[PDB]
Amino acid sequence: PYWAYSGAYGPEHWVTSSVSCGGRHQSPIDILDQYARVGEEYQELQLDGFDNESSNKTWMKNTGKTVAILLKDDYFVSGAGLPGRFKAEKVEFHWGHSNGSAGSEHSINGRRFPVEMQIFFYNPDDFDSFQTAISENRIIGAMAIFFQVSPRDNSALDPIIHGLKGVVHHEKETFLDPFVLRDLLPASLGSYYRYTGSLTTPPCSEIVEWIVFRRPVPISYHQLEAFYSIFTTESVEYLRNNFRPQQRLHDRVVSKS
Image 1 (cartoon, rainbow, N blue to C red):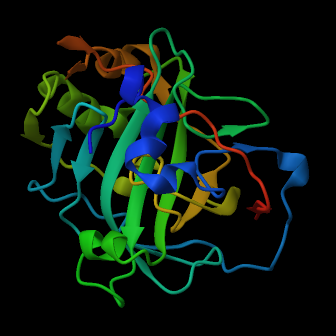
Image 2: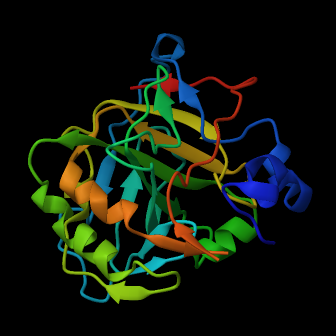
């Protein structure tokens, strides 16, 4: 079903086509740190494969709603209260309008960031593929990483920024220079929030265990310009402010490491 980030098919109308979008446990949310429960003693995030350079087969697409990276290497996460081990499938990005304006889906104490990168994972022990996993409404995992402006270019982002320059037009695809996935995550992985939520685009399935990192990854204002230059169609517009409005916590508790 067609959906958009504004207009008659905008987020307040998603529920018409995708019923889950009007559910009680939706994402993204604002995280009030005061109300985050230190909760269980949880195994620290265990990352496998994140230090390896990416395959030259890894590629990036302008979907018109985001820019997605389809991962071609094996990356695994466990710990942080997730049930078992999860395998990374893809990366997507949400950003603002100009000059570092708010673009994140999540926030912390009302504070937004100019970009939010989300990495999506499925449990390979249960299914052969990420698509299989979503079709069955089983638990999938997602990490949310904020970017924050810094005076210098973040060299770790170079291959991603270069990719953006190659996918300005809707539907365009490009291979990416090798990057190290670990280096697109915060320097410390020790500080994060956990909650149960949903996909932030239709079908808005309420099956996502979110890990939201508290500390951001740096990006320069110059690098941000590569996001602001992306186009989307349907009629052409800049692809900007591509974030879903925040959803109510309701009966949920957010945990923190």
